[PDB]
Every structure is written in C-alpha cells, then in structure tokens.
Length: 431
Ligand SMILES: [Zn+2]
Ligand SMILES: [Zn+2]
Image (tube, rainbow, N blue to C red; front, side):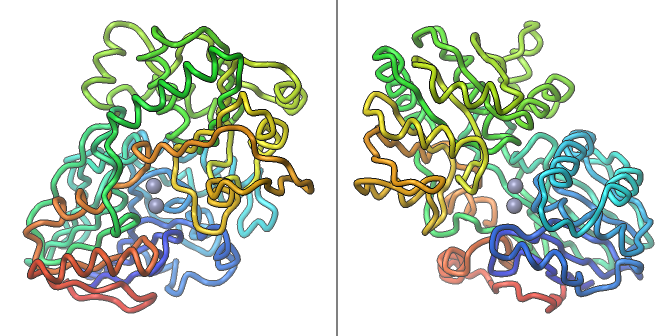
C-alpha cells in the first residue's frame, strides 16, 4: 500500500493523491492548481488517468475538484464518489470554473462526462474495491466535506483532506481520525493557531454598528462557496441588534450556493439544523439581496450607505469587489473587513499595511476607509487544532500548505515523537 502525492506538495493548490493498494488505483481528490501555478493544469497529471479504478472527493472546492473534468478528458471513465452535498456543490463549482476561465484546459463535454460518474457515498459508508475498504469521516470544512480512511493489506491510511476550523458555528466539528499507520494531512496554518471565534464575532458587530450608524458602507471581500454564507449566518443571528441596512451579496455564484443550502440542512451543525427545524433559513438575514448583474452592481458604488457588501474574489484576485473597493476605500466613513487570509504580496496585505494609497484597477486610490482583519473567521484547522487531530498518530506526511508553514508544524510533530515528512511530488509513500 503506497500513497503518491500528485499535488499540494509544499503548496496549497493541486490536491490529488494516488492510492495504490489491493491491486487497485484509487485517486484521492483531483483539484486544480491556482494563482501562479495555474499553468500546471495544462501539464500532465504524472500518472495514467486510464488506470484509475475509482476516485474520491473530499469536498467541492475547485482546488480538490478542478481537474476532475481533465481526468475524464484524458480517458478515465470510472466512478467518482463524494457526499451528496459535495456532489451538488460540485456542479456549481465546475460550471463556474468553465465559464469564468481564460485558459480552459477542459471543456463542457468533460464537465458533463465527469458529473455523469458521480455516485453518493456518505459518512460511515464503506466502499469496497478489491481487498480495499474506504470510508469518509466528518471533516467539518465545507458542507459534506470529509477526510478519507483507506484500509487494506492489514494497514490503515488516513487522508485528512481539508480540516475545518472547529471554532466556527456553521459546520459540525471535525471527527478525530482512527488510529492509523500513515496520516497524509494538510497544514495550511501549521505555523500558528487561529484567533478565537467569539472575540472576532464581537469585534465584527462593533464595526457594523459604528459604520452603519454613521451611514457608511461595510465592504467584505469573500469567497462564494462557504465564507459568504457564513458571514450571512452571523448577520442573521445578530441582525436583531444591528442597524437596518440592505445586505447586498454581490456574487451570483454565492447566490447559487446559498440557494442550495436548504437542500443541505443535514450537512450542517446541530445549531444550524435546529434553526432549519424551526422552519427558518438562518442564512438569509433580513435585508439580504443577491445582485445578479453588472449594471446594478456598479450602481452600489454611487449609492450612499448604510449598507453591507459581500463580493469576490475573496483575495482580491479580481471580481466585482475591486469595483467596490475602488470607489469606497477613499471615504473615511466606510470600513473594509477581511474575513479570510490574505496571502503575502497580494492587494490584500498591501492595504493592510495601511499605506497612504493603493493601486486598484489602473488608478491610485487614497485609503481612508477603516481596515479590519477578522482572523477568527479563517478557514482551516489552525496549528493547535492540527496538533490535537494528529495526536497519537505514529507517522505523518504533510501536504497542502506553504513549505515554511508545513515545517513549523513538522517541528512540533517531530519534537512530539512523531515521524514526519513533507510530501514530494510524484514520490509515493508506503503505508
Ligand atoms: Zn477547502
Ligand atoms: Zn484546499
């Protein structure tokens, strides 16, 4: 039994790991590379897509699902398991990646073909392939997200997939993994623990009252798949103490996702499920308004506050948000609220550095709006959470994360008596 990293090696995008065992070849995730590595989606997988006996998806994020169509484009015609939630989310995530994609490395024929082989596999349901036994575990990172438990040949392997931030309220807490011979885990935040959720939420409310009371705009750059709706849930459970103001979710995609959440009630925490039982949708706070097209979206730049605006991309890589920031960052009555990690050297960090001005869409725009970073809203299991999850596991291979973040986690692991290494592209590891 060997597990061969084929992506997310000393990096965060690309997640895809080939499991060789029981005389079968099971592919764990098949995501695309993003940002600078984006051009590697045109290169070959590094293995023979036609020799895979089945593939498993831990969640719908494009970076674990993005290359699936390519896998089908190049031959594969086997099954692709995922939780029903991932199965449905996946459709929205792929269609959008197709549409909004300059250098397409796959086409509509592939998406269709790819979605055609999806089969539901829910938490605690064992798949059988040869002498192999596989099962999903509650990962708590996205609705219907899981870590993989692969067993066979008397050995046990665990692929963490992405582990969510247990402090947040929307998804359920990650399940501990079973005792295993090898754990292939992520380490997106292996260097530090997360800022407490409760205190971030409180600070968030303060920012909203001060800004909206003064007639200002709260600009919140966010991702469309889970962060957006999570902010809405917080606006729903606290909107009772917040000044009345429209909440514009300026993301069609975030819309499509939100529309789908009621079809996924079971995929959320007890808290969230209790709200749905009362017959209420806790993801639609009073005043919510999904904006569909440009014309209305641009209107928001000229309209006065108070208002709360959610728009992508979550890392300012582009998207409707740049247009809001452009016209709003100059007014001191506004507030910018980051609810996701802003990588180094990005327009995000640049603004957080509080310079006198910033360059957005071809112009130098004074930065007078207030800036705030609500780290307690960050996505992955932070370092402390990583340590607890990994606890008691003999060997650990680290993937998904910047080299330095991975090492930091390694150090602690090493010092804990745990055998650790940093996955290398193509180099398989024995279980
Ligand atoms: Zn993810
Ligand atoms: Zn990921």
